[PDB]
Image (cartoon, coloured by chain):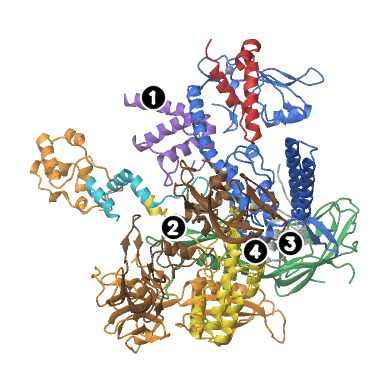
Chain colours: A purple, B blue, C cyan, E orange, F green, G red, H yellow, I brown
Amino acid sequence: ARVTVQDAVEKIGNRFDLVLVAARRARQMQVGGKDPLVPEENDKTTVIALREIEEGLINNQILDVRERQEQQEQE
Amino acid sequence: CYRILGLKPTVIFADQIMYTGFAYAARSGASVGIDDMVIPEKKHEIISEAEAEVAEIQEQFQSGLVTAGERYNKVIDIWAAANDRVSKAMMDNLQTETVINRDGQEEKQVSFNSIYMMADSGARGSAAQIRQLAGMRGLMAKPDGSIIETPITANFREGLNVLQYFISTHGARKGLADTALKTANSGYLTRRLVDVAQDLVVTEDDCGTHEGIMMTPVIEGGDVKEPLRDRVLGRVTAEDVLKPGTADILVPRNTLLHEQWCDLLEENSVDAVKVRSVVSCDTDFGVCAHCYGRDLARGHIIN
Amino acid sequence: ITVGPYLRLHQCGLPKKMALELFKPFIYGKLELRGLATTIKAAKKMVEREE
Amino acid sequence: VLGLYYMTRDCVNAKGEGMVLTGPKEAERLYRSGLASLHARVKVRITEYE
Amino acid sequence: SVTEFLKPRLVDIEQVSSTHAKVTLEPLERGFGHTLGNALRRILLSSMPGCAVTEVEIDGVLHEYSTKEGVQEDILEILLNLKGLAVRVQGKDEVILTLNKSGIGPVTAADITHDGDVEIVKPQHVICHLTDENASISMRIKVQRGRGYVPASTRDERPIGRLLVDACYSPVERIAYNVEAARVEQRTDLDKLVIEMETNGTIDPEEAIRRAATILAEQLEAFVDLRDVEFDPILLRPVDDLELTVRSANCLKAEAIHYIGDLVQRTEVELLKTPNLGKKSLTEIKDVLASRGLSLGMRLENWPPAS
Amino acid sequence: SVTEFLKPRLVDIEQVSSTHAKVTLEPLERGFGHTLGNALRRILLSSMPGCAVTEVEIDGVLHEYSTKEGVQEDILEILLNLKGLAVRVQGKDEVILTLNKSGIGPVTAADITHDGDVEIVKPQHVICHLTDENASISMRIKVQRGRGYVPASTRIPIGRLLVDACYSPVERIAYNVEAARVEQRTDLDKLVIEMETNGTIDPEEAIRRAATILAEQLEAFVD
Amino acid sequence: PEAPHDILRLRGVHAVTRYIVNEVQDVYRLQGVKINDKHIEVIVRQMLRKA
Amino acid sequence: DIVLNPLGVPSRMNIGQILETHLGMAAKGIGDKINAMLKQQQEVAKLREFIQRAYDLGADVRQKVDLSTFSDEEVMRLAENLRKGMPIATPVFDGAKEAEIKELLKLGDLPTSGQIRLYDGRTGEQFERPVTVGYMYMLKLNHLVDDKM
Amino acid sequence: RDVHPTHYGRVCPIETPEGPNIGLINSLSVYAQTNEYGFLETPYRKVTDGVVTDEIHYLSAIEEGNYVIAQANSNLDEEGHFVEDLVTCRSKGESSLFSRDQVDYMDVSTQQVVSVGASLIPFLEHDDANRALMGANMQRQAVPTLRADKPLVGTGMERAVAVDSGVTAVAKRGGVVQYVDASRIVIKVNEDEMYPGEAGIDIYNLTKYTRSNQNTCINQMPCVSLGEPVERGDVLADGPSTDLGELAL
Ligand SMILES: [Zn+2]
C-alpha cells in the first residue's frame, strides 16, 4: 500500500470505489476513535486503511454491517 | 514484463534498469572528439564530378539546346544524386571496423565509434544530423520556398564560409517564427476539441447492440501502412469470427481482443474483423464499456 | 528543477524551506498536540524562530 | 540507453574469450577482477523460468 | 608462504622541493598496491589537519568594500592574499599575529612580528603594496587549527571593523600514486607503491602518511568486531497551584484529577454532568484557567509523562 | 577534536539465507563509505584464502572433447559441476579424492570416498548422471589450497583435464552508499554491503577476515 | 475532393467516420505520431448529435 | 573542474565547443611549459627562445612578433603574464585549422588527439575509453535560484 | 520577420530575440553606417584592372545591386591580383561564379556580416545557426565576478569592446604615473602636450562599489604602477568584467 495500490484495487475491483472506501475507513480511524485491525507500524491512517483492505478485512459490506450492529447496540 | 508479470515487478525492473545503465555508461568513459567525425575520402571526387556535370549542362543551355526550367531541374537532380552518394559513402565508412582475429587473420565488425554508437543505439542523433556533421549540408531553400541552385558542399567539421552561412540563416530564422505560430494555433485547436467533447462519460456496461465497424489493414498502393493487429487490439468483437476455410466459430461474439486473441488471429490469417465502436452505440447520454473497449492506460476494460 | 539519480519512481526531492512554508497549519496542529505549545500564538512564535 | 547498449555488445577478439562460466555471478566476479572483458564471447549456464 | 602476506615498509623519502615529495612503500603483495593507494589518496586529500587565517582587523577600515589611502589593493584583495598565507603553529590551537609596516614598497610575510611558536614557511608571499611615503599599515591577524573547509557564513556579536575569512585548513594540494614492480631477489610478484605529494610546505610527508594510515586503521575496527550493536512546565503543576474554592477543589479531588494537564483535557459537558459541580463552580474553574491562558477541551498525546 | 572522527553507531545485519547477508553501517564521515567499501570489496574478491578443485583425471577420457558412454552430460559439463564443489581441508595443502560409481541415477558429492580431513559442505551437489545400468564412472580429483582465482588459460602428462580454481569463499559481493544525517550534520554516509559465500564460512566471518587482512597491512605506520 | 456532408447523406455514418479517421491518421502517420482510433471516433460521434 | 554530458553535442551540432576545448588545452599546455621554466629559474635566453617558438607557430599567419626589440625586463614581465596560459585569437570566419591546433598540442608535449586517460576518483579504476579533457570559458547567467524559489 | 538578401553587411542575421519580438529587433553590423538620408550602407574595396586596390566606397542597397562583388575568402597575390580565373561573387541578389575581369568590388573583412556580439564567438563557422543565436543572446546576461579572467581563446575583438564601452579609465594625454592608489590616479603630463600657463597633471577618480540598473557592483581597479610611462589612449583602470583592457565575461 506504500508504493502501489494494486492489491487494494483487485480486492475492491474499481479504482474509484477504493478511494471512497479507504476515505471512510481512514476517517473512522482518525476522528471516530476506532482501532486498526492490523499492526500499526508508524503509518498514516490513509495507508493503514489500504493495508487493511489488502488483507480483505474491510470493504463496503463489512463497514455497513458494523455500522448497523453498532447503531443497534447503542439503541 | 508488464503484459506477463503485472505492475508491481515492472516498477522494480525500471528502477534497476536505470541504475545499471547509469553505472555502466559512467564506467565506459564514452566521449566525443574531433576525430570521431570521419569524413569519407570520396567526397572530393563526387563533388568534382557533380560540378563537371552541371558545367556541361550550363554550356548546353548556353548553346541553346534547352530552356531555363529544364536546366534548373537538371541541376537540382544532379546535386541531389551527388548528396545521396556522399551520404552513402559516409555511412558505409563509419559503420564498420577491422579487427585482428584469434588466428592472426582479419575480421570485419561493427564499429565502436562514439558518434556511431550514440546514433545506432537510439540515445541521441538521427542520420541527417550525422550527415550534416560529416557529409555535406546539401540544398538550402530560399525564403519563398525555391531551392537555391548550388548547395552547401561543406559540413560542420570543415566549417562554412560567409556566403553558405548567410544562406543557412534563412531557414534557421523561419523555423522559430513557425514554432511560435504553431504553438498559438495548437492551443486553440485543443481548446475547441475539449469544449466539444467535455460532457461524454462512460455510464453503462452493455447496450446490447449488434452493430459495428469492419476493420481491415491500411494498405495504400503497394505499401501496407498499418497491420490488422495494431487496429483490433483492445476492442470487442461485434460478430462471431469464422475460420477462413471452414465456417467454424474461431472467436465468439463479445470478446475483448487482447494479445493472445490477436496472436490467434494472425496465426489463422484473418484479414477483416467486425468490432464495436462508440459511434454505433445505443446508449443515450454517454457510452457503454463494451462499445469503447480497453482502457489504454491500464490494460483492461474501461471502468 | 534539478536531477536526482538516486530517487525511486514514487519519490521527489523537496527543499525544506518550501516544505516549512507549505505545511504550516499541519505543524501548528502537531506542535499543539504533543504539549510543546499550549496556545496558537506559542506555536506561531516557535515556527517563526525555527527551533 | 547508451550504457545498456554498450554493455550488451560483443567484440571479435576480447580478453577472456572462450571461457565456460557457472553462471552470471562468476561473470560479474571475472569482470570486476579485470580477468575478462565486458564484450568477451563466452558460454554461461543459464536457468530461466516460464 | 601461502596464507601469510608480506608487510610493506617505508623504504625511501625523497624531497624534490620544499613542497613536493615522494614516498615509497615496499614490498606489496599482488593487488594490494592499488588497494592501499586509492584509500591513502582519498584520506590524504580529505582529512588532513592544518592552520589558516580566520579573522583580520585593520587600523582604520570598517568593512571589506572600502579602500585605504596609500595602499594600491582593495580590502577584498588583501583578504584574498591573507587567505593564502602558510603558517605553522607549534604549541597552541589559536594565535594572534601582528603586522606593522610603513614606507613605499611591498608588504610581505617577512614583515609579520616575530613569535616563538609560529613559523612562516614562505617569507616572500606578498600581502599588499604601499605607494605613499607617509602611508603606514597596522593589522592584527588571527590563526587557528582545524581540518576541512569552513566558510564564514556558516559560523556574542562582532564589533564593527572585524573582517571574516573563509578557512581552508588542508595543507595537501595534490596526491598521485604509481604501482611498479619491486626487485626482491627471492620472488617476482612483489610490487612497490610510490606516492607523489604536493603540499603548501606546512606538513611533513611521513607524518601525513602515518596519520592517514592511523585514520584508516581506526575506521576499520568496526568490522573486525562486526556485531549487531517535552511537555510545557505549566502542565506539570499540581491543581493546588490554582486558587480554587473548597467546593470546586473537593469536586476535582473526587474526580481523580490531580494535575493541570489532566484537568485541561476535560471538556465542559463532562464537568457539567458530574455531580456536586454546578454552573458557578465550572465558571470559576474556567476563570482560574483563563487567568493563565488555558482552556478546557484541549488534547494531548502520550500523557502522563511518567508523573 | 581535530584527530577525532565519527564512528558507526547503527550497525545492522539481515540474513537473507544461510549464505546470503546484508550489513548496514551508519553514520560515517563524508566519503568514507566509498573508501571502506572499495577496499573491502577488492580484498574479498582477489585475496581470500581457501581450497578448491584444480584438475581431474577420467579413465575413459583422453581429450577435453571426448565421448563417455552411459553419462547424461558432456565432459565440460562435468568440469562445470566440479568447479562448484565446496570443500574444507584440515592439516594439508593438497589432497586427492577418488570417485567410482556404477549403476543408474544421479552421482552426487556424497559418493566421493570418505576421508578423515577433507569435508563436504553440500553433499547433495550433483556431479553427473548415469543412464545405462552397465556404465561406470571413475575419476580422480585434486584439491589444492590457495587464494583468489586462477584461470586455466594461465596455467600450462596425458589426460590431465584442467579446472578453473576459485579458492576464495566469496560468491558475490557488492556495496552501496546512501545519505545519512545527525541532528545537525546533513551530508554523512551510510554503507550497505550485500554478500554471499559458498557455505564454507558465514558472510560475517568473511567480512571480519577481510578487515583483519587490511588492518594487518598498515602496522608499520599506525600509531 | 469529396465533402463529408455528402458522404454522410448518401453513404451513411460508417462511411463518414471511416473517411475522417483515415484522413486524420494520414496527417498524423507521416510524422510518426501514434494515436489510437478511439479518440477520433468519440469526436466524430460528438459531431453527429443533431437530427 | 566540470563534467559535461557528451550526448548534448551531436544532436545540437554546435561543434565549436569541442574545437574550443582542444585549443584551450593547447594554450594551457604552453602556459604550463612557461610556468615550469619560470619556477626553476632559467636564463632569459631560453625563455625568449621558447616564447618566440610559440609565437612563430602557424601556417602563414598575418601577425609578426619580434622579441629582439624587447628588453629583458619586458620579456620577463611578458613571461610572468603568460604563465597561466597563452591567450589565442581566432577570427569568426578566418580561424585556426585542425592542423594548427595539433601542431600547438605537439609543442606542449600533449596527445594530438586531444583525449587522455582518466581514472575514477572513488575506485581508482581507469575508464575504458579515452576522454576529451580541455579548457572552456564558462559564464554565470543572471538566473539565480535565490530569486526563483 | 525574415532575412532579406539586402541585410548583407548592414543587419546581423544571427542576433535577434527569440520569442514574440523575433525579426522585429535587430542589431547593427560591425562596419555599417548611414547615409545623409538615413539608409544603411557598407564598405567595399574597389577593383580596377583586376587589381584589388585600397579605395573604400560605402554602398547602399540601391547602389549595390548593380555591381558584381567578390568575397573576402578570395586568395590574392602580393601585388593585389586574384589567383583563379573564376571567383565567387554576388550580383542582383544571387551568387555564382564570375571571371576575373567581371568583378567590380570586394568585401573588406570576413567579419563584415556579423554584429559585435556574434563576432566574439570563436569557431562560429562550426556551429549551427540556432545554437549561435542562443549563445549570442546568452552572452550578454552574464554577471561579473570577484576577479576577471581573460578568455584564453578569443577572437581579437575584446579590446575594442572593452575600450569603446566607456567602463575603463583611458589616458587623455601621455605622461608618467606620478601617483597611484586604489581610488585615484595622478598622471604627470609631458610638456609636449601641455597647454600654455598650466600645471600639467591629470587626475582620475575611480568608481568604487557603485550600484547598476540591475543591482550589481560597478568597481574600477588600477592596472598601472608608480613611475611607469603611459601613452595617449592606454588603459589606466579596469572596469567590471575587464582584464588589462580586454573583455572578460
Ligand atoms: Zn454500446
Look at discs 2 and 1 and give the one toward the viewer: 2
Per the rendering, the mark at residue I142 is 2
Q: Which of E124 and B297 lies nearest the eye of the viewer? A: E124
E36 vs H99: above or below: below
Residue type at mark 2? Answer: Ala
CA neighbours of label 4 inside 10 A, class few (<14), some (14 to 19), many (20+) = some
Look at discs 2 and 3 and give the one toward the viewer: 2
C41 vs F124: above or below: above
Residue type at mark 3? Answer: Leu
Q: Are marks 2 and 3 on the same chain?
A: no
Quarter of the image where ligand 1 sits: top right
Residue designated by label 3? F85
Q: Which of E135 and D13 lies nearest the eye of the viewer? A: E135
Residue designated by label 1? A68
Q: Chain of mark 2?
A: I
Look at discs 4 and 3 and give the one toward the viewer: 4
Residue designated by label 4? I80
Disc 4/disc 2 C-alpha distance (Å): 43 Å
Q: Are marks 4 and 2 on the same chain?
A: yes
Q: Which of B81 and F64 lies nearest the eye of the viewer? A: B81
Verify CB contact (< 8 Å) between mark 1 and mark 4.
no
Disc 1/disc 4 C-alpha distance (Å): 108 Å
Measured as percent of width and height from the top left, residue I169 is found at: 37, 68
Q: Are marks 4 and 3 on the same chain?
A: no
Disc 4/disc 3 C-alpha distance (Å): 88 Å
Would you say residue F194 is visible in this rendering? no
Verify CB contact (< 8 Å) between mark 2 and mark 1.
no
| Image quadrant where residue B174 sits | top right
Left/right of residue F57 with respect to residue E224 in the rendered view:
right
Question: Disc 3 on helix, strand or loop?
Answer: loop
Disc 4 beta carbon < 8 A from ligand 1?
no
Measured as percent of width and height from the top left, residue F2 is found at: 40, 75
